[PDB]
Length: 342
DNA sequence: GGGGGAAGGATTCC
DNA sequence: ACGAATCCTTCCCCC
Ligand SMILES: Nc1nc2c(ncn2[C@H]2C[C@H](O)[C@@H](COP(=O)(O)OP(=O)(O)OP(=O)(O)O)O2)c(=O)[nH]1
Ligand SMILES: [Mg+2]
Ligand SMILES: [Mg+2]
Ligand SMILES: [Mg+2]
Image 1 (cartoon, chains in turn orange, brown, blue):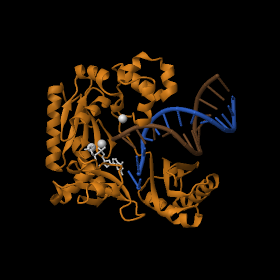
Image 2 (cartoon, chains in turn yellow, blue, red):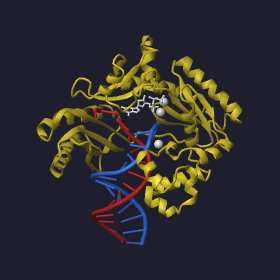
Image 3 (cartoon, chains in turn brown, cyan, yellow):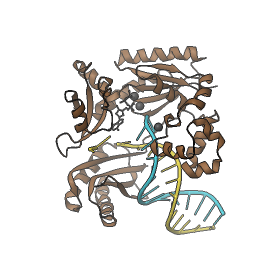
Image 4 (cartoon, helix red, strand yellow):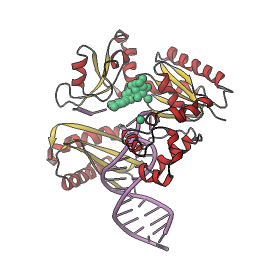
């Protein structure tokens, strides 16, 4: 049958940083996202291991990071750089299969069935690539291998960091029975919690529960996903993905509900989006506001034709007035998101 | 009943 | 105390 090779760059934003200024290596590095409300407001996007050991990981506030690691190095996130670096490395991989699916910015799936014969020869294609990237770009990555993508990826979770690990058919079997259901991709907290209830601690526990009861609990897509996966037969292919929407959301120096002080931030959002669209022309537009108590409200609109920048400016204002109208809370973060490209 | 599709919220992290 | 794919629920027009 089939073999998939999953590739995941290690602590990616932090590592492109150690590469551009090697002096940093060995020290605690933290790439931040300074929301600019007050010195050090914002969360951490990621940090190298020489700093993640103390709990400083993606998500925690930068103020909390400084209390733990007062003297670590804090850099702001430079997306475009990390982005052009990922692109280079993605090419490098095509020179191994042109059946490549690019998941996110730091990971890819390769279908190496027509280039390899077995897990012994695959492991080698594996080691070979890491080298081709540690030499060409200087970035270490982890590599997972197995039958379907899910497992290939789970393989990389275990081999992190700078690892490579194969998961052969005997392994699948034991994992389907031993692996913790929460460690299966696409199963965040809200779902693991809903599974505990139904009494499903493992992937296998799904073969002993009335499907229609499962469906109502977590949804049908998840039910079929999990069930087939457990029945040892998940096999979705490696298709090339495309950008389906682009957007930008920004944080205001302070809360508000005054359509006048909000307009500026909103046009910045729209501006940064239309630039980072390029060529592409959207038929749908949405406005998104994050209320004072961290909840999200959104209002959109689809047009029979594409949207001109000038129209974006105008429809964003209506949708924003629709939000402020139907909601009492103050708005904290405001932005836009374009979808349905022609 | 049931397709087709748009809206707005929920969930994930890839 | 910081971008986006996918899916679910709901509403709706129409045959
Ligand atoms: N802004 C922001 N960026 C995030 C967040 N989580 C992940 N990222 C970004 C920055 C990470 O470098 C990039 C790759 O994510 P990974 O999950 O693979 O983690 P990273 O590679 O940082 O560590 P890893 O070696 O995989 O354990 O995704 C987040 O919560 N906020
Ligand atoms: Mg990674
Ligand atoms: Mg990743
Ligand atoms: Mg999980």
